[PDB]
Amino acid sequence: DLKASSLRALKLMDLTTLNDDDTDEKVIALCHQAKTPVGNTAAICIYPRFIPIARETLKEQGTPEIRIATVTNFPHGNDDIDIALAETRAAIAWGADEVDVVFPYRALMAGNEQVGFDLVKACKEACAAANVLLKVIIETGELKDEALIRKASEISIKAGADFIKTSTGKVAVNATPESARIMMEVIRDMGVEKTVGFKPAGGVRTAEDAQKYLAIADELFGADWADARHYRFGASSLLASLLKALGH
Image (cartoon, rainbow, N blue to C red):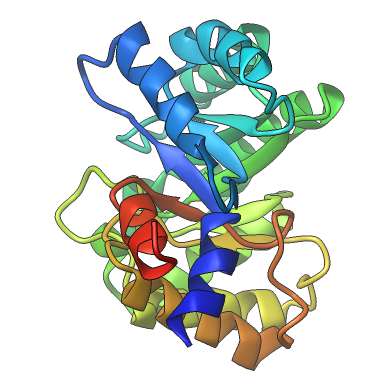
């Protein structure tokens, strides 16, 4: 059971390092770790300034198709569209393949549904022009309430999110199976399973955890649905756990 799930999960990872003090050496090591004896991860996820060195490293190890994701409006999800859009434009200029933007979840909690639409839509228009995929982090662990998780997911989808993502990994509570079910049910209910992927991020630690998340996807959308365009794990230590489950 865990061998099959761990293979699938490894090739869906956005292998991540997002620390206040990351270095080129740490990003280089991360790129090397993304090329495993059983597969490449789907992507790496790093701060924008590291995109050039990561791209070089990925090319020089012969894995040019590992995608490079980054983050914007991060981790705060503030409601200043000009700043979020400037950061998204800078991430595109740094060379990102994918931008994971934080939704203005505290503004939503205060009753403003419109700013989240306008922020996501502006970032989507910049990314789409550059053929860059946009993921939207709603911060389920701070929204807390099921109705709010559903609403943030719905606004993000309406505004053009290519993925909805649970969490930044920078707050106390990140992905859970409960939150994942709620968000994937929104994808289902809105009829967007073909065009909107799901990404649990933070707190996915073990091969057993990953197997749970994939079981929800398979139940809701069928076993064929999850793939790199539709599913990612935002994770780090998970990779060593998946490799261990696979005998490496």
